[PDB]
Amino acid sequence: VNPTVFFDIAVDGEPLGRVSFELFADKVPKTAENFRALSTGEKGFGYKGSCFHRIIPGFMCQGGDFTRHNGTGGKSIYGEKFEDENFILKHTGPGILSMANAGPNTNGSQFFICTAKTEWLDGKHVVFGKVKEGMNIVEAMERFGSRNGKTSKKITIADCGQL
């Protein structure tokens, strides 16, 4: 029943590979639906063509700022921001998909893919999915990151949608 969406990743416009995600619509339906719709672009805006602006190896990959490309933008399908839906699910290890935010109830479109267990984020960031296929591709992306998060090459979402 839970939806699966994919990102096709490019590095300086060179294809890298495909990452797919299971979204936990059974446990966080509002947050899952935002990401699903941003991935298909069915509301008229979304993730296609956007970059991962912050990648810290041994920590996370962060993206979803499709309006300013640097961590200061983005918007949800519900408006500029929406509430923290629940914190049922925890940051248990690599492959977890969690919402970036700027305080309580400030979810937009930014998300991160954890590449480590990040338990200190539990109860503060809404977990809403997990990598299903292509974790090896996330690991390859990680290698273009750095300690301060700047990427050495431009890591983009070349295509995305629902499988």
Image (spheres, rainbow, N blue to C red):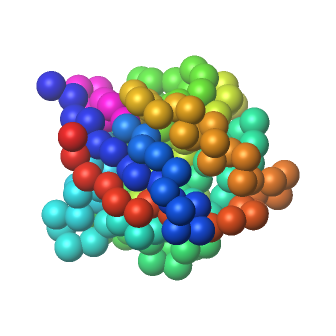
Residue sitting at 26 percent across and 52 percent down?
161
Whether residue 144 is visible to the viewer of this picture, yes or no, is yes
Q: Which segment did they paint magenta?
A: 21-28
Q: Is 23 positioned to the left or the right of 130 in the image?
A: left
Residue 138 versus residue 52 in the image, above or below? above
Quarter of the image with the C terminus is top left
| Residue projecting furthest to the top | 92
Image coordinates for residue 121, horizontal then vertical, percent: 63, 35
Residue 56 versus residue 148 in the image, above or below? above
Quarter of the image with the N terminus is top left
Residue sitting at 67 percent across and 29 percent down?
116
Image coordinates for residue 56, horizontal then vertical, percent: 74, 48
Q: Is 7 positioned to the left or the right of 115 in the image?
A: left
| Residue projecting furthest to the front | 14
Task: Report the number of discs.
Answer: 0
Image coordinates for residue 137, horizontal then vertical, percent: 54, 40
Whether residue 99 is visible to the viewer of this picture, yes or no, is no
Query: Quadrant of residue 92 in the image?
Result: top right
Residue sitting at 72 percent across and 62 percent down?
151
Image coordinates for residue 155, horizontal then vertical, percent: 58, 61
Camera-side residue: 118 or 160?
A: 160
| Residue projecting furthest to the right | 147
Residue sitting at 31 percent across and 34 percent down?
23
Camera-side residue: 101 or 137?
A: 137
> In the image, is residue 25 part of the stretch drawn in magenta?
yes
Q: What secondary structure predominates along the stretch shown in magenta?
A: loop
